[PDB]
Length: 129
Ligand SMILES: [Cl-]
Ligand SMILES: [Cl-]
Ligand SMILES: [Cl-]
Ligand SMILES: [Cl-]
Ligand SMILES: [Cl-]
Ligand SMILES: [Cl-]
Ligand SMILES: [Cl-]
Ligand SMILES: [Cl-]
Ligand code: NA
Image 1: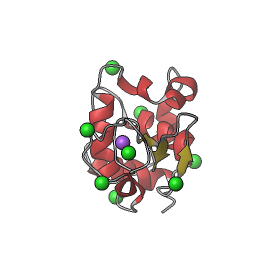
Image 2: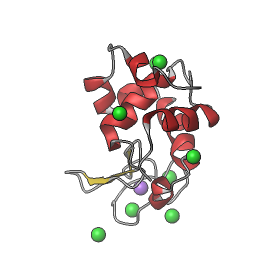
Image 3: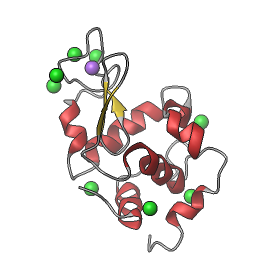
Image 4: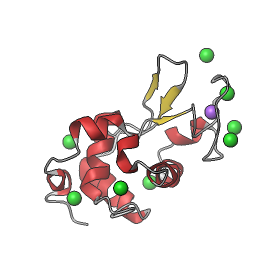
């Protein structure tokens, strides 16, 4: 599913992501924009052989199982395919664990490089939330 901007903001808020660990909704929407362009089916293979899955490009090295990332963990206790669903619940629950892991949203390099420090409220501006 390719979400609209406000549509994703609303779904993220529904699932408790707004201000989670102090990160406002616009930070989450901005991260999803640059990770997946709001496409739940996005996948990308990393140099190390792991793969990133879903709207927030969650990595199989630590967070989900895809059966083909040697030496990896599955700390969200989910198949990586769960992260590609039109229903964002699995991605949101796993992102909550990732953002709690010590480095906040810096876990998402694209968030650090493209969202951090910017006017992230632009991403939810206008939305009925
Ligand atoms: Cl957009
Ligand atoms: Cl915001
Ligand atoms: Cl594996
Ligand atoms: Cl393969
Ligand atoms: Cl594990
Ligand atoms: Cl699995
Ligand atoms: Cl949803
Ligand atoms: Cl933080
Ligand atoms: Na894994």
